[PDB]
Structure formats: C-alpha cells, structure tokens
C-alpha cells in the first residue's frame, strides 16, 4: 500500500506466490476446489450455465466434485455476484470478464475429455468430439486441431520437429497439465490486471507491505511444496532474529549497559546456505532437470554424494514414526523435516504439450492468447532436443523463479521496518474459548514466538517497554517516577 | 534471472561459431570462424580503415583480405585471432557486455590441458566475465538427447570424433578422431562434379557447391546397388539452378560424396571409416559397458545431417556387432546444434550454478581451478 | 511376537551375505560381501558424494572404486569394512532398526575366540541390538537337515570345511579346512574356456563365466570314461548364448571344472581332495562315532550344488570306508542356504529364547559372556 506524501492513499500492489494448482484437478474427500466453480454452477446468473455449456450438477465435472460440493456456511449464490461485481469494479473489460468465465469452464470440460486406445495399437485416440467441441469453442480453438496436438504431440528433437505419439495415460495426464497451467496463468493475469488498475499517477513516498503466507508446517509427508514454504519461513525467521538483534543492541546502547552479542540470525545461515547456495539442494535439483534422462533416484544420489557426511544440517531420514518413506531430512530452526523426493524432477520441469500451447497462442480468445505469450517468446531458445530453455526465456526450474520471487520479496522486506503478527489456532475441533495444548505449543515453536522468548532470556528474561513501564509503575515513587516517565519517555523509567 | 537470462553459450567450431543465450532453443548467432586481414590499403565508402574482419564480413570481402582459420581440427591454434572471434561474438553478434554475463564455452575431445587453462586466462583476464565453464562437445550433445551414457559420433567441419561417455565422464582412452569432415566433403563433391563435365570457375560457382552438398546429398543404404540403379537411370537424377539460369544436373554423385565418410579411400585416405571407428571405440571400452554404448549411438554435427546416414550406420554396426546385441542409432533433427542446445539446457539448469568457475575461484586458484 | 517376528538371521560369507527374518523359508537378502571405495572424486547424476559402496552397488560400479573383501576364507579380516556390510544389511537391505531386533549371526569353524568376542562388542556396543547369538555354520547346516550328529562338508566361495558334529558339539580336532572353493573354481573354468580358444575380454565377458559354471557345470561320476566319452563326441556338448549373440560352446570342460574339487592337482594344489578329506576327518574321530558320521554326510554350500556331486561322493567314500559300513551322502536342494535356514529354524524356536545373549548379560559379563 503505497501511501502518499501527505499520508493519504496513493497505490497498491499485489503479488501472488505458490498457488495450489492441484485443487483444480483434485480434491481431498472433505475438501473442495476453488469456489468459483461452485459459485458459477450455483445458478444465480443462469446465462452463464448455458454460456459455458455446463450443467448445475457438479458431479458432471470430475475435476471439481472429487471431494465435497456444498458448504453450509457459504452462499455460493451471493458470492457469485460479489465476485462478478468485483470484476467490474476492478475495471476488467466485459470481454475479459467473459474470457474469465468462458475460460474457467473450459477447464471443467477438460476433465471430461475422454480417450480410448486405438485398436492393435497402444495409441490414444479420442473417445468422442462432444466435449472437445465445447472446450474448443469456449477457448476459441478448433476441435480437431486440438485433439490431434493432444494425441499426436508434434515435438522438435534435434533441429526439426518430430511427431510423437502418446498413450491413453499420457493424454489424460497432459490434459490435466494444461487445465492446471491455464488456470494458474489466468490467475496470475487477473492479478496483474488488478495491479494495473491499482496504478495511479499520483506520487508515492512510502508504502506499507502486508505479507500473508503460510508458516512452517510439518507433515509426516513432506514434499517439494513443503520445502519451498519452509524455506520461505526459515528465511523470514532469520529476518526477525536479526531485527531483534539490531533492536536489542540499541537498548544496551541507549542505557549504557555493557552487553556483547552476535547476530541472532547467524544461527540459521547454515540451513539457508544449504538450500539456496550453488551446490545446494535447489541447484542439484535444477541441474538434473537439464538431464534428459535423469531420475528422482538419480537426483537423490547427487544430493547425497555431495552433501552427506559433509553437511551437518543434512541427514538421512528417520523412516519411522508417523512418516511414510525415506529420502532426506533437514535441520530447520523449528526442527527436523523429513523430505520425500518423488515427482520433484517433473514438478520442477513443468512439462506442457507445446503443440497445444501453440493453438492457445493463436486463439480467437485474445486473453487466452495473451496468457501464453511468454511461453511463445522463449521457444527460440530451446529449439533443439536437450539444452537450456532459458536461452529463449523459458523456465529451466520449478524452483528457478520461486527463488527469484522470494528474493525480490525478502529485498522489499529489508527496505522495510518489519512489523510482526502471528496468528494462532486453538483447537482442531472448532470451539471458542478452548485450546489443545500441544497443538498451540507446536505453533509456538514454528511461529518464532518461542525463539523470541529464548533470545530474550539470554540472561535478562523479562524486558519492559518504557511507556508500558511508566504507566504501570509510576505510582511507586509516584512523584519522581511520573516526572521521569513524562519528562522523557525513556529517561523517565530511568 | 541475474544469470538465468544472463548465461551465454558459445560453441567454437572449425567452420562455424554457434552462440546465444542459455535458455534459447537454438543459437542466436551462427557465423564463419574466420578473421580476414586486408591485403591492401584502402577503404569501403563511408567506413574507416579496418585492420581486421571477422565472420561473414571476412567471407564477403574475401578477395581483398588474407583469410585465417583460428581453430584447426577443433583445437585453437591461433590465440590472437581467437580473441578476435570472441570479441566479435560478444560485442557485435550478441551485442552484450561480457563483464556481467556468465559464459559456457565448449572444447574438443582431447583438448590439451594447457588450452583449457589459456581460454580461461583470456575469458577472465581480458574479457572480465563474472564466471565461466568449459564443457566437452560430445558430452553436451549426448546430454541434449536426454542421456548420460552413450557414444557420440560427432562430425562437423574440420574433425570427426567418437566419444564414449559413461555416466557423464567421457572416456579418454576410447575416443577416436578422424580428420575428414564436411570441408573435405565439399571439396570432393567439387571434383566429382567438375569430373561430371563442369566448371566452378568464379567464386560464385565455388561457394554454391557447398549448398549443393547440403541440399541434394544423400547417404544411401546399399550404396552398392545404388550405383547399379544409377546406370539403369531412373528418375534418381537432380538438377539444381545456379545463381543464374545454368541448370546443373547431379544424379548419381549426390551419394558418392557421403559414401566418402564410409570409404575414406575415395579421397586417398588410408584411415578406417565412421562405422568401423564407432565400433573400434566400442571394442576399446570396458566389456560390461559395451551393451550401453551400442544402444546409444548419438549423432551430432553438420556433416551427420546427410539423410539416410542413420540407416546406413544402423546396418553398418549391426553387421559388425555380436547378434546378442541391441544396436540403436539416435540422430535427432536439430543435430547441427546438439552441442549448443546441450549447453543451453545445462547452463540454464537449476543445479549448474554450483559448477560455474567464478572470478573468486580464479583470482584465488589460478587457471588450474577450471582445468579440473 | 515381540521377538518371534523380530529375530534376524545374518549369515556372513566370503562371497555372499544371506539375511532375513527367523521364520522365513529363505533369505530376504543376498548380496556380495564387498565394500567399494571410489578411486576418484566425482558424483552420479542426482546423488551426492559417496564415501563408500556395499554389495551390488559396489559390484556394478566396480570400474571407479577399489573393491575389498572383509571376510577372507570365512574369517573377518577387516572390522571397519565388516561394520559397513552389517550397517548396509540392517538399514538398507532389511530396512529394520537393529535396536529392537534380536540378531543370530554365524561364524566359521575354528573362528578365533577373540573374533566372536569382537563381533559381539560391535553388535551390542555400536548397533545396540537387544540380544544376539553366534552359531557355527556347519552346525546350522546339519540341524536344518533335521539331525544332530553327522559330518558336514561345507563349501562356499572362499573355504571348504569338514565339521564332524556329535549331539550338537562340533569336534574341534577333527575339522579340516581346504582353501579351494567356488571362487577358485570360476577362475579355473575361465582358463579352460579361454584355452578352448576363447576370450573373456571385457568385464561383461568375465562375470558371465561364473554364470556358465553355475548353469552348465557337472560333477560326473566316472570322470575317467567321461573324458573318453567326450572324444567319441556324443551330444554331451552345451552351447550358452552370451550377453549378445556370440554363442559359446562348452562340451567337455563342463565337468573338468568340478573334477578340480576331487583333484586339486588340476590347479597346482598339493592338498588332498573333498572325499579324502571327508574320510580323514572321520578317521580322526572316536571309533564308536564313526558309523554315525558315515551315514550322515550332509552337504551344504553354493559350490556343493554341481549336479552328481553326491553320487561321486557316495562312491568316493564307499570305496575308502570299511565294507561293514553304511555310507550316506545327504545333499538337500535348498543347500546353498542350509546354514541360513538352520538359523531361521533355531532362532524362531520355542526353546532358543533362553540362549539369547542379552545386553543384561553383556553389560554385566563383558564379551566373554557369549564367547562360551
């Protein structure tokens, strides 16, 4: 929030990190996908239903009814408008406001796209042009061209373009990949477009950043996504520990106490380097992604040969307890996290059928066309089989950005006066006035709260802020303590 | 992005330089590996006196300059003239300033230790690049075809090589070099085409024999009963129209030119040919790794682009290899840039960052550092 | 169940480790008894730097590591490298945590007192197992064939032994050790097969001579008129197809290899052979127990698996033994795991619980406790 010179509002700026792409295609049993879907099928704006070519029964869209469909505390009908109206206010063009919708339905349809094995062949052949037709139209595509690209992905290995055939299992999976890809991008776009409106000409002198992200969560199962988040947090933490060190040291300087101490951040640098530094996890992760014939297993070994025994924060797992398999544990400030490396290579490659993307790139639906541009502009760079996508501006890592973004962030965080807020969850059971112990205890460790207490206690536990000191105790030598507190907010307590 | 965008990949060849940004799919810059020095004093209209010319301006103006090739058979032979080609690559071709770009370079198969140290000395000390890295060419070609073990038959403009690679380490004692490549091949076509009763008299006749070789040449399988076919005279013939009308016909010689790669005897070479050499490399390697190499004959290089090269090689080594073996000749379409693409991939990779030799490593360890 | 499920059985050999859970019918884990140490610095793609390799990863990657065998002739010779093979067995092969599993181990026939105390020191003090037990190998083989008195001819990869056992107590002064086994036997086949006019040149040729020995080798009875038979050339010959097509033929040598076990003179050994040694063990024992040993020649070990080994031994000792005697050569089918199976039985047994050495016994009595 970019405040002006006077002190009155001037601009805003959003940025999104780590979106749960999986919901779009999946959902746990007690959960559900994004609201939008359920919003739309609610039927408050019936045109929409016919416009998108769907029904009102979610069980027609596998992608979005794997879990739950309705939530009592939510009125999908009301929201739909909220949403709707917001779009408008946000300045979106009707068309775009149309793309959004139309595009959000295509995705539903995709999950309905079905295929079958060609006879005597292990190839995938379309099981009908019922749905494709809709998806095609809704996206400003051609049914055929689409089903081909999907089935007979025309690749470019060597210096040419080699037409490759896919399996049934391969298609279903690629489709899902686009569905997710498209949704994401779109989401990104919306944000940008928002930002665009939120751009004013008026001068800006300062801003107030409000960061909302998740905190270090430990699961019996920790995958790639966990690392990314944990890493974010372990950084954020150090960010604090330092601010505190800086802060602390001012008092002892203001007062005249004689206390020497090392930055509290330092304690964490070990873990961070191991992740973000050159021969660290990410790198080994993002290099192997360049090896056309690497395995998760491959990656794994590379991870060890290089860090195992040589690095302290690096450890081989404890396979048992509440954990599900073995690969590698790390020693974060909050504790030991047991990480499972399986899918990483892929997840990190963001494999997308480029033939299809092609089609998008030349859609009749501008917006859809837009969203893909940046993929279309780096292809120059990865023209032949093997090599480096970055040559043409294509991502080389699933993780290559995350880092870039996380840096651009932690940098923005520095030219800032950090203000901290830790949100807590009392009981899993949803009951006011109650608290499970160990549940809150957990949070406290991973929060930073327990670490702030530590650093405090190093020592001189309780530390009173001066005004907070005046008020409560003035009364003790009332005359002389009040005078002190009033006369100099600090000098007073003195 | 700092260097995600920023990594450069320069593949130095005997005939062509391929260059561009790690990330791209193909080289942003491709140009001859020449440095022309004017034979006389004078100027072009509007320009100043130029001491030197590089790449295409050296080729185009060849009549008034003495042309020189810095890389003889894949090895840098003149370091004054190579620093000139690099300068041209950064500043004119890619138009980047080198002192803020990491640079991945390539070297040849048994490139002398001292050279890898010298181009590092010139990269860091005269171009002041932040960091650099030298990859071996066959090794980038393999890797660009996804794998890590295989044997690459690599063939460009001045050299042919066989580099058996196992889990990434190129095997020094099994590497073979055959000094007959696309350059030799254009000059042989030249003679079998003048010998067809022709004349490549002016320089506009000379240059295009090379464009005939690229467009119309073939590697026939059963080159035996292809000559026999030539004689019955089928519609096998192929006429090319010259810079002007002068429609030249090439029927037969069309494949007599790449049959030189299997029979060096066509050109007074006593060395063995491509397929035998693939094989000999292979019976020079460990026994347990020979099934791997056989199912992974990756081809790269401009001269391996002749259609039907792969089928001839397929059958050439099946019939020399023990029948219990699986033969597999991979020849991708982008192969004239495999090497480069393998570098683009690798250098844009997430894990490569920790192998870049930085000026910190160098100023502290000497050229020895990158030499490995 | 606490330990009914929970007892481990680890049989440490010169060539192979056999491991698994007491209760099972056969070893869950079988793998070479090697520990590889990399000759150079570097990594596999995706892995970290590894200081060491064990079992099959050491065999597969043998070209870049220095391989070492911890057990020479059945005795543990390097304790740093053995603790490495045990670690691998528990944590990677059986994937169990050792500190909650009783462990039955095996040792060799005249295993030095000090070793049985040392592996106990390492089992309890570095692996922290709840309880353990060391059985003698021939003794588990016998017992797995139901009985308690007999003489075991035990023959694996580095040693052969004869261990006369009476009501369970192996008889120290009658035990014979012959250092010629399956390892020696693969290398002799190697030479009689190169000598047949062949070449096991690459490492993929070396390894498979051992798979020829296992699949096609025989112990003929009347090895005399089997050579004679070879000459008339019957359909006695046998061709094996190599990793590739290269069909190698082995007619005769097929049995010249196990005739080495009866004639050590085939390999420049001056020692006596298997059958004479069975016998000599027996005329070194008490007189009254010799009818028992003769009717209970139990065979165990990978190298006693050559078909017709039992018939040759049957007739070999009948014709050395007094005719008043009953000869009986028991050779079960699972014999390459007799030792292990005997341990599985014993350790899963209802009465064995009271012989387990517990950490209570150890922390209180020192390694002496299990040493007996």
Image (cartoon, coloured by chain):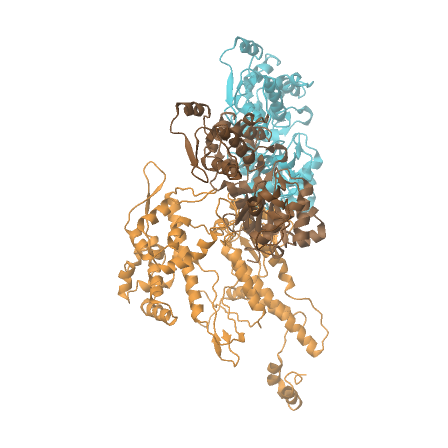
Chain colours: A orange, B brown, C cyan
Q: Quadrant of residue C202?
A: top right
User: Where A423 sits versus C189, above or below?
Assistant: below
User: Where A289 sits versus C278, above or below?
Assistant: below
User: Where A433 sits versus A302, above or below?
Assistant: below
Residue C43 visible at all = no
Taking the image as shown, residue A133 lies to the left or right of residue B192, namely left
* Residue at 57% in and 20% down: C295
In depth, the one of A279 and A480 nearer the eye is: A279
Q: Position of residue B53 (x, y in %)?
A: 60, 48
In depth, the one of A413 and C33 nearer the eye is: A413
Q: Position of residue A114 (x, y in %)?
A: 32, 48
Quadrant position of the C terminus of chain A in the picture: bottom right
Q: Quadrant of residue A121?
A: top left
Q: Looking at the image, which residue sits at the far right?
A: A258
* Residue at 46% in and 71% down: A199
Residue A372 visible at all = yes
Q: Position of residue A257 (x, y in %)?
A: 71, 76
């Amino acid at each position: 929030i970019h405040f002006g010179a006077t002190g009155k509002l001037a601009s805003a700026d959003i940025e999104t990190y780590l979106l749960e792409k999986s919901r779009v295609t999946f959902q746990l049993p007690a959960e559900r996908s994004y609201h939008i879907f359920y919003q739309i099928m609610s039927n408050k704006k019936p045109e929409l239903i016919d416009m998108l070519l769907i029904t009102t029964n979610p069980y027609d869209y596998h992608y979005v009814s794997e879990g739950e469909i309705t939530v009592p505390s939510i009125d999908d009908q009301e929201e739909l408008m909220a949403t709707d109206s917001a779009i408008d206010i946000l300045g979106f063009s009707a068309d775009e406001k149309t793309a959004i919708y139309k595009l959000t339905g295509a995705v539903m349809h995709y999950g309905n796209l079905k295929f079958k094995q060609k006879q005597r062949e292990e190839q995938a052949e379309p099981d009908g042009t019922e749905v494709a037709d809709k998806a095609a139209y809704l996206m400003g595509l051609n049914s055929a061209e689409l089903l081909k690209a999907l089935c007979y992905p025309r690749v470019g290995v060597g210096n040419e373009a080699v037409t490759k055939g896919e399996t049934v299992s391969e298609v279903h999976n690629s489709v899902g990949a686009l569905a997710k890809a498209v949704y994401e991008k779109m989401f990104l776009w919306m944000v940008i477009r928002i930002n665009q409106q939120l751009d004013t000409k008026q001068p800006r002198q300062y801003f107030i950043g409000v960061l909302d992200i998740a905190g270090f969560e430990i699961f019996d199962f920790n995958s790639f996504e966990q690392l990314c988040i944990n890493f974010t947090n372990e950084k954020l933490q150090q960010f604090f520990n330092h601010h505190m060190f800086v802060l602390e040291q001012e008092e002892y300087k203001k007062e005249g106490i004689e206390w020497e101490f090392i930055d509290f951040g330092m304690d964490l640098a070990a873990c961070i380097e191991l992740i973000e530094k050159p021969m660290g996890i990410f790198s080994i992760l993002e290099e192997e992604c360049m090896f056309p014939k690497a395995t998760d297993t491959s990656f794994k070994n590379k991870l060890y040969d290089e860090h195992l025994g040589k690095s302290n924060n690096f450890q081989k797992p404890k396979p048992a307890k509440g954990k599900a398999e073995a690969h590698f544990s790390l020693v974060h400030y909050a504790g030991t996290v047991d990480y499972n490396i399986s899918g990483w290579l892929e997840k990190n490659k963001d494999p997308l059928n480029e033939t299809v993307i092609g089609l998008y790139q030349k859609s009749s639906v501008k917006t859809l066309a837009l969203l893909f541009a940046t993929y279309g502009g780096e292809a120059e760079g990865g023209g032949g089989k093997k090599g480096g996508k970055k040559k043409g501006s294509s991502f080389q890592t699933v993780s290559a950005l995350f880092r870039e973004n996380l840096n651009k962030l932690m940098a923005n965080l520095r030219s800032t006066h950090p203000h901290f807020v830790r949100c807590i969850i009392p009981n899993e059971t949803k009951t006011p006035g109650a608290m499970e112990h160990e549940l809150v205890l957990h949070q406290l460790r991973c929060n930073g709260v327990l670490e702030g207490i530590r650093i405090c206690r190093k020592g001189f536990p309780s530390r009173v802020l001066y005004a907070d000191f005046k008020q409560r105790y003035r009364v003790l030598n009332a005359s002389a303590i009040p005078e002190g507190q009033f006369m100099d907010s600090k000098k007073a307590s003195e | 992005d700092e260097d995600e965008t920023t990594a450069l990949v320069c593949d130095n060849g005997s005939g062509l330089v391929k260059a561009g940004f790690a990330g791209d799919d193909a080289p942003r810059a491709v140009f001859p590996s020449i440095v022309g020095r004017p034979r006389h004093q004078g100027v072009m209209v509007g320009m100043g006196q130029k001491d030197s010319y590089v790449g295409d301006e050296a080729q185009s103006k060849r009549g008034i300059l003495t042309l020189k090739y810095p890389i003889e058979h894949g090895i840098i032979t003149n370091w004054d003239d190579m620093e000139k080609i690099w300068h041209h690559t950064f500043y004119n071709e890619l138009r980047v300033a080198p002192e803020e770009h990491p640079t991945l370079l390539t070297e040849a198969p048994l490139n002398p230790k001292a050279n890898r140290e010298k181009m590092t000395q010139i990269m860091f000390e005269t171009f002041n690049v932040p960091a650099m890295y030298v990859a071996i060419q066959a090794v980038l070609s393999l890797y660009a075809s996804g794998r890590t073990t295989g044997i690459v038959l690599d063939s460009g403009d001045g050299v042919t090589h066989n580099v058996p690679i196992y889990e990434g380490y190129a095997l020094p004692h099994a590497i073979m070099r055959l000094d007959l490549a696309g350059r030799d091949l254009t000059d042989y076509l030249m003679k079998i085409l003048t010998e067809r009763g022709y004349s490549f008299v002016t320089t506009a006749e000379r240059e295009i024999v090379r464009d005939i070789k690229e467009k119309l040449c073939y590697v026939a399988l059963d080159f035996e009963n292809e000559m026999a076919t030539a004689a019955s005279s089928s519609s096998l013939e192929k006429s090319y129209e010259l810079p002007d009308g002068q429609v030249i016909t090439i029927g037969n010689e069309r494949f007599r030119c790449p049959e030189t790669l299997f029979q060096p005897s066509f050109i007074g070479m006593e060395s063995a040919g491509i397929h035998e050499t693939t094989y000999n490399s292979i019976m020079k390697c460990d026994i347990d790794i020979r099934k791997d190499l056989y199912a992974n004959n990756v081809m790269s290089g401009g001269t391996t682009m002749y259609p039907g090269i792969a089928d001839r090689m397929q059958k050439e080594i099946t019939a020399l290899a023990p029948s219990t073996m699986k033969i597999k000749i991979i020849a991708p379409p982008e192969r004239k840039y495999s090497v480069w693409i393998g570098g683009s991939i690798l250098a844009s990779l997430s894990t490569f960052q920790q192998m870049w030799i930085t000026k910190q490593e160098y100023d502290e360890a000497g050229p020895s550092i990158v030499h490995r």
